[PDB]
Image (tube, rainbow, N blue to C red):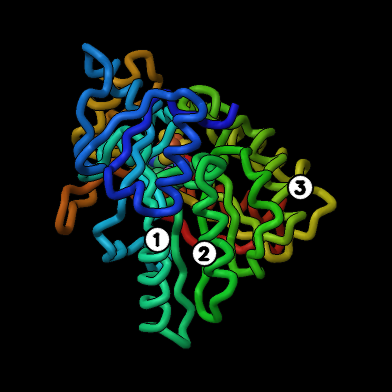
Amino acid sequence: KPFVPKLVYFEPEALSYPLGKELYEKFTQMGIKIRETTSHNQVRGIPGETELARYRNAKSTLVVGVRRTLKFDSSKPSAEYAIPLATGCMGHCHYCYLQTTLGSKPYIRVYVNLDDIFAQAQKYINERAPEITRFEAAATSDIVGIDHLTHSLKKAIEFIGATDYGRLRFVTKYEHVDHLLDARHNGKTRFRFSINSRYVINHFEPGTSSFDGRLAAARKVAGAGYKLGFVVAPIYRHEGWERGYFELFQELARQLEGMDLSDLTFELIQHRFTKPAKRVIEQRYPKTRLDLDETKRKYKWGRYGIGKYVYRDEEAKELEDTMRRYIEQFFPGAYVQYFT
Ligand SMILES: C[Se@@+](CC[C@H](N)C(=O)O)C[C@H]1O[C@@H](n2cnc3c(N)ncnc32)[C@H](O)[C@@H]1O
Ligand code: SF4
């Protein structure tokens, strides 16, 4: 069940680094089809005659390259910066906002020059010290779901664990966390899981681990000493959402009863979509129940790029207040970091 690619691309320069050498040896030993590419941002010859075929095949394709853009993007409100360990995901969440993010690729991409990346991370920490600097490792990927192949996240966790003023955080929809349990995190990593109503998970989250799988992993990471959190997103106003999300928090509390939840955190993100989302999503998921009706939404204009549609102010406030009530009921003391 853990992700294994059916096609792997390598940058020639990637083989000069330990991870690239290790991955090349791994996949050749497995007999998997391996190709060369000049740049990880320009991958040619992904099989498929239709757009849907090429998209689906890309989702089973791994690309191993070198990170050359060492300037870290901002990752607010989650963290100060996004640490770039990987990009892309094997999941097929119908609503995934990465689909329409500028310059996003459907294939999974891992970076091998971890010395350069952690060194730059340390520079950002030093620049802000003694203030705390948080890094988001899953801003443009499901870093946890991919990590059993590389252990790049494990190395990042222990790198941050050794720092005085550095903190790490990431969120996942995958249960494959066994290799991370003995990591020397030193209490400086927030391990989060994306959760949602039964409606949203069943209809819009194929190719990910089940709710029970995510919670089993949540119990594992909490027992291993990680700081635990949840991300309720996308908060989606489906038919019967009020009761749907009520039963989510009720079941979440039931599956976490007995554990210490004094330092538990919640993050809330309402469903959002961009102008090109409808054409992209309808092409990739023709039978989706996802409502992308812009006429009943509020548009927030972009700054340097394009904007996004979110629920109207009164609908958004209704979602926020209701979610805060459920968290207050089932998890008293737990901290809601934000609603957006
Ligand atoms: C980009 Se997701 C990367 C991390 C990992 N692969 C994961 O799924 O947890 C980060 C979060 O954002 C949510 N999310 C994704 N799309 C949307 C969206 N369109 N509207 C509102 N929220 C959206 C997802 O449910 C995640 O909780
Ligand atoms: S698991 Fe996360 S990154 Fe992957 S498709 Fe779903 S929302 Fe997107």
Residue matched to label 3? 256
Q: Position of residue 208 (x, y in %)?
A: 53, 30
Q: Earlier in the sequence, mark 3 or mark 1?
A: 1
Q: Are marks 2 and 1 in contact (CB under 8 Å)?
A: yes
User: Looking at the image, is mark 3 or mark 1 nearer the viewer?
Assistant: 1
Looking at the image, can residue 158 be seen?
yes
Residue matched to label 1? 83
Query: Crowdedness of circle 2 by 10 Å Cα count: few (<14), some, many (20+)?
Result: many
Question: Which residue lies at the image location 40% right of the left edge and 26% below the top edge?
Answer: 60
| Left or right position of 9 against 247 | left
Cα distance between the residues tagged 2 and 1: 9 Å
Question: Which residue lies at the image location 46% right of the left edge and 26% below the top edge?
Answer: 204
Question: Which residue lies at the image location 38% right of the left edge and 23% below the top edge?
Answer: 33
Residue matched to label 2? 168
Please tell me whether mark 2 sits on a helix, a strand or a loop: strand
Q: Position of residue 110 (x, y in %)?
A: 39, 45
Q: Amino acid at mark 3?
A: Leu
Cα distance between the residues tagged 3 and 1: 30 Å
